[PDB]
Length: 172
Length: 171
Ligand SMILES: NCCC[C@H](N)CC(=O)N[C@@H]1[C@H](O)[C@@H](OC(N)=O)[C@@H](CO)O[C@H]1NC1=N[C@@H]2C(=O)NC[C@@H](O)[C@H]2N1
Ligand SMILES: NCCC[C@H](N)CC(=O)N[C@@H]1[C@H](O)[C@@H](OC(N)=O)[C@@H](CO)O[C@H]1NC1=N[C@@H]2C(=O)NC[C@@H](O)[C@H]2N1
Image (tube, rainbow over all chains, first blue to last red; front, side):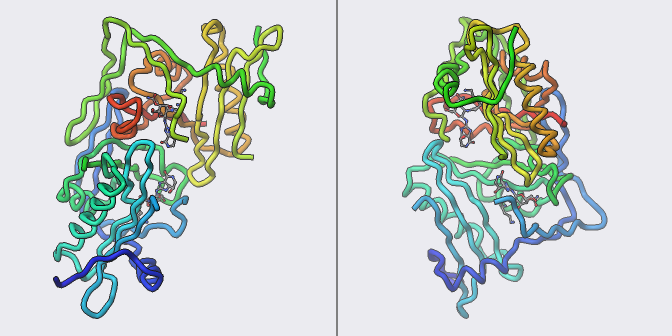
């Protein structure tokens, strides 16, 4: 019980904001576009890519969960979003604080997302991940997500141009 | 044979009747691997009948209309601009059942392209179900290529079993 999980309250919103999800990676997922399909291959990059997410990301059925340590600091969060149309719970964000990884916070937050999904009658969880976010992709694969598609054009004209939006899902 | 203009309130009821329901002897089959996605056009026998659902789950917006002699709508396109990624979404483009093979598709998409360059768009983008081979062939003809897909988009919908394919082209 190193970490407790609960619905986020107003005092958590400011702590959530500071966990921006910025990462370093020695690998990226390269997207190869053919006329008849798309291939993902993990490739080493030297020196390591430093990715800071932009301040402008282009943005009852909503919910934010938070992982809290003994001193009351937010160690992680997930913001989820339900669309009844296709029974999709979108994992809009999931982050673990830099110094709190390898302690089952990721799994715990996703388990709370899954609880909300079954509460709303969702058929699948779904998330967007940039092809350069190899650490997150490995984390999502570990938690049972698989690639369900991509949009190689989504980040065109954005601060993230050169990257591809990869889509992952899992049933519940 | 056909003139193009911005759609007016009296066109809304005619636009509604043009749902784009089709028959096809082929579909684009989606193969999911752990490391990617493959699209292969495959014959289906007997022909697939696709009726689009009434519930589709839905300055920078614009609707164009193709008009014949006698002033009847022969087709339309609704487009949508997002400055964030300079994307003009072709939200819908349909030609009336009896008016195909007359360059209405091309004409409507040319009006979409004019709006894109007017707004400074970097690319056009559309969604098409994998079973809509006729539309996919039309879009390929007009210069669109596949830029991705979402095999999970239609889960829990009337269209479950189909995959949402994404196509784009630069301006
Ligand atoms: N920020 C922490 C991570 C947040 C989550 N993982 C969600 C995510 O992936 N957001 C990414 C990320 O903010 C960043 O992408 C890169 N590569 O940095 C920017 C591009 O600059 O695009 C975002 N994507 C978007 N898709 C949405 C869309 O289609 N319509 C509406 C609008 O919401 C769109 N924004
Ligand atoms: N009439 C011709 C179609 C013209 C266009 N290309 C529009 C299109 O493709 N609509 C399809 C089509 O209505 C149908 O799909 C099948 N397979 O029939 C249903 C599945 O029931 O899903 C629609 N898609 C959607 N995507 C959107 C989304 O992501 N969020 C919000 C909302 O807008 C969503 N709706």
